[PDB]
Image (cartoon, rainbow, N blue to C red):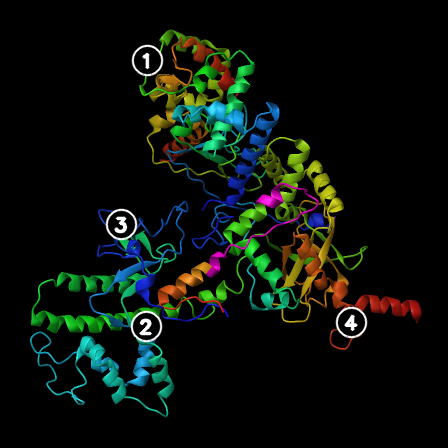
Amino acid sequence: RNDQGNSIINECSIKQEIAKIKKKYNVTDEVMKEFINGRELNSIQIYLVKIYYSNKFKVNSNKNDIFYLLYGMTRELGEMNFSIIPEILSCAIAPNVRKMNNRKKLVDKIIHSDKYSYLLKSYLPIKNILDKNNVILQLMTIKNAKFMNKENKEVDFSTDHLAEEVLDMLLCI
Amino acid sequence: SAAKKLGTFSVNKVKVSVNTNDILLNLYGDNENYKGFPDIGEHIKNQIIASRRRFDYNTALYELKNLNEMRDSDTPFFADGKIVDIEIFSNVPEEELKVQKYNEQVLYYINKQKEFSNNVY
Amino acid sequence: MGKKLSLIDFNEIYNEENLITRANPIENHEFSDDGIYSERIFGSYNEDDDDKDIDTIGWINIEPYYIINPILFTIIKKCIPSINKIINYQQSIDQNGENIDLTEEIGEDDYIGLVKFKDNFDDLLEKYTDKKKYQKEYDFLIENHDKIFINKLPVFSHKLRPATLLTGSKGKVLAFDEINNYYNFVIEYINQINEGVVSDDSIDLLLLPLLYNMQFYANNILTRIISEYLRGKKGFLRKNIMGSRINFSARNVITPLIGHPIDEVAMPYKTFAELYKFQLINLISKVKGINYNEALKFWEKGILGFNQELYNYMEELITKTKGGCTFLLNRNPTISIGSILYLKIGLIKKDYKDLTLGISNNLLSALSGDYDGDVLNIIPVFDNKMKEHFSLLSPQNFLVDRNNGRFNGDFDLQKDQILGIFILNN
Amino acid sequence: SFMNLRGLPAKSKNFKEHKDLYSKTPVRIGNMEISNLSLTNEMGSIMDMLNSYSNNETNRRELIMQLLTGNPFDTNIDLSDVESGTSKILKSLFTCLGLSIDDV
């Protein structure tokens, strides 16, 4: 049915990725406990994790592996202009999970991006119909929830920040 | 030289199915010339005729991306030679094909075949 | 030692979770969770993620009336001839009818059914006992009161059972192997007993023949599931247990080769690429440095069309390995001494289209082959301890004749070289 | 390649549908194969090989794990003692027959 070869290849890729995360930021178990601070899995969060490592591998969804993956992932964007998105990934999920509306002006600006334009060009065969009925690409922009940060904080920011930085993130796709 | 003489032909017939789920890839040519399978004059390259990606609604954000490059978990077909003839059977209305960019080659071939049948009739 | 026969008591074995209740295998176009096709206990056919193993055992209650076990039944028929007639209840006219109206009473032992026979089992055995012929069987019965009557009936994994739900052209056909068929009857039959809650003599007049068919079907089950599952070469005991399938294997056709010592052999590039796939993937991961997935992509591109770099990688691999990446060559069918050989790879063929396995001429006789088209099989060897253990299978070991202790004639010079040396000498 | 319902190697239909470049159908070891392999006094070694290749799922998995990483030139395999799938399914055969298992 399903061969074990590619699955074990993916697992070993996961293990070496964890090794690199440990090597880069001299992290260990204790800082890991600090970063989790008693949090649990967030669906859109693991989805972002899958997006960021899509080219590298497929996520196995093991718990501690996911948390280490987010540690490395969050710091990784922590280096460059990404400012607020890592803060959101730091937060835990608030219980107001819903789908707020989208600022159509910002999404139009997204369409204006020649970067995203050439992505559409690489998705043009899909773009011609599948998006027209329902664009999966920005559908997650509708799917915006509320977060409850561990530092007694909640997410309250303009959507331009994800509009720009997640655009860069698809540029990393 | 003698071995070069003992040349022998070989012909293969192979059929591929495309459902609503699986989609083809632009293996051959640039963006403008979307051809997942070599044309009549073309020779099959890299011992691969075409390939299909198993589309999923959920996996539309990572896997379906980079359509030009094949993904690891796909279904290719393998052969060698030069295309001699093509025969397509379609059960879907042509409107979808019209709004399908990744089905322009099959639509073109279907139009050619239909024109042939019209002329013969 | 080994796995020992014993009809150990099922009651201390049995578990409440595995007792199946009466239900049809299918239910509203979905497998019932209470029948034989239960997913609660019993695995999932399409999905292999089921944490619980395929070796889960299903289970059926017959505690109300204990039943002789089928396995000892044939032995029983030996100790007491025609016990099938004793348990066969024809002494009934309410529902069975007058029928023949003339029968062999045999001291009223016959037509008493299963319950009475169980009640007077010792007396019947005393009636039918041969101290000269059946004494051993009666003794083995003596050591086995606890196991004669069985109170629990087991059922195989539905994943093990090849029975499937096909969609026949007439309609959806539950194409089961015959096993569950009788099992279904069995459980359906036991349904009647748990259906027969109301108490009345005529019910027992029908209930006892139901027990007769219970034992008949139990014997049916044992004979049937021993007919094919564990009998013959199709059977499981010989097809897999002794020898099985191998996941790291290949096979090819042999052609002559010269310029090398007898031990060295060459393999076609494609088959070597496929066999040691993970060695190359390891080296390519180390040297490229990127994750293993893109390495797998590169290896795919490498087997697809000829590449110089990948050939260099395999050349490094053959050069730097501890044992030289040896393997086993065996010639179907192996019926002679040393018909298996332990050979060491010496050279990778560069020509992509070449697919034949080079082999030195002097090994033709030992493995009893010819270049006419024989297909020979290769099994790679990986573990270093395995290399040392199989070193005794190297042709150098077979060079000495285990028959007479002289130089072996199979490694002696063959035809053409005999001729040539003769020209040189004489 | 794809394993069968018994968690064992089995051939497939990809080759006919032109999904596989090479035929890739495994070889099976038969009577005289086990016999001649047991010509050497290494029955434990033969059992180890059979368990590592196909019979035992855990053993084959640990073989791939050890073999993928580590030195490509030197392979130092390590094997467990988990009961093989064949032995367990034979145990199921016997127990469901009314037979049982009892070593020594």
Q: Do marks 1 and 2 share a chain?
A: no
Vertical position of residue D61 compared to residue C369: above or below: above
Q: Is residue C270 left or right of residue B31?
A: right
Q: Depth-wise, is mark 3 or mark 2 nearer the camera?
A: 2
Badge 4: residue crowd in 10 Å (few <14, some 14–19, many ≥20): some
In this view of the protein, can residue C214 be seen by the observer? yes
Q: Position of residue C282 (x, y in %)?
A: 64, 39
Q: Residues within 10 Å of mark 3 (few under 14, many from 20)?
A: some
Q: Which residue has dot 1 on it? A: A101
- The answer to whether residue C250 is left or right of residue B24 is right
Q: Residue C388 at x, y = what percent?
A: 71, 58
Q: Nearer the viewer, residue A127 or C394?
A: C394
Q: Which residues are magenta?
A: D65-87
Subunit ID for the residue under disc 4: C
Measured in 3D between alpha carbons, the distance from the residue under mark 1 to the one under mark 2, in whole angstroms, is 72 Å
User: Which quarter of the rendering shows the C terminus of chain C?
Assistant: bottom right
Q: Which residue is mark 3?
A: C33
Q: Please name the residue that numbered disc 4 is placed on.
A: C408
Structural crowding at the residue carrying mark 2, measured as other residues with C-alpha within 10 Å and reported as few (<14), some (14–19) or many (≥20): some
Gap in angstroms between the C-alphas marked 1 and 3: 44 Å
In the image, residue D41 above or below residue C304 = below
Q: Would you identify the image quadrant in which residue C281 lies?
A: top right
Tell if the residue under mark 1 belongs to the same chain as the one under mark 3.
no
Q: Are marks 3 and 2 on the same chain?
A: yes
Eye-nearest disc, 4 or 1: 1
The kind of residue tagged 3 is Asp
Q: Residue at x 21, y 57 (%)?
A: C22
Q: Secondary structure at mark 1?
A: loop
Q: Which mark is residue C147?
A: 2
Structural distance between the alpha carbons of marks 3 and 4: 66 Å
